[PDB]
Image 1 (cartoon, rainbow, N blue to C red):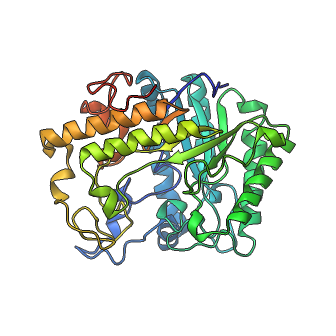
Image 2 (cartoon, helix red, strand yellow):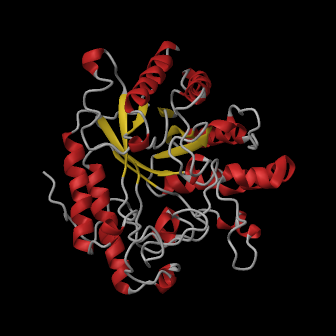
Length: 394
């Protein structure tokens, strides 16, 4: 359904749909705010569903699930020149642990989305974005500040959920739409046992193939250096149809944020040069236009921004207020952003392609493909260049 050697992935993530992220849909979290006090806002989906109870959580999510992404967005994605979508989903859509507060029902919408993808000639990756116990402690895993994916039976339950995803979506029914099943989004390499993580990856790889599936297995890089996975899941060991997913951003640390625009572009070009050297097919599964960490709650509910020196002990760079609204952006920030997007697009098209995070946000412009495209900051057509050849690839 896809030629990783010849075609280039040009997609967007359908984030904030099946896994709630506070910075993407702040209106679902804001009702819990007491005036200016943010101490009572649930910090993740786990706490959001627990605080609401099953009845209200199901009513609010059914409304979110049915309106956040619909068939019209798939038509729009296709009309903009995109050929792929990445769909994050948490383990709770398939199985609940005893005492889990999550509600189900996401599957019905996942299946509707696969038919919309088919109708619009869009290919997809199904991404297991959150595992039981949390694989990274991020709010996008469903459970913030916990790192227990490798404790107790959490790894085995993840494998059972993947077996379900393998039997339903890795067979012949969706062979023309599904071009990858991503085993686990962002396992936080530095706090996990890497040997157990590789064993988990190998177990998922073997389990999928054992079902008769030929679907590409996508492994996230677990924040390891470029080339680290060169010797794992290789054709020399009879392991094939494997893709490495790299996520790239330059706003999650004081050092990265302080770079001038030329240095940000140099780093983006370098991502293109180093990925070219890897031996596995690779795709930049997540990246954005963000040059700051100013979007409200991007670092998590009740956490400020490093950009204005209000978090993770970073120095003050500038005020975030003026960057919250794209209509207030200075002419220089608009040019810097377009330059940054074009450098990234060239670097990722140098290898397997790219998937922007994300299609839409309620009001965070740096993270919304729709908003940037409508304001002329994201090239349209996507091959358009106002700043051609900033990297000099050969």
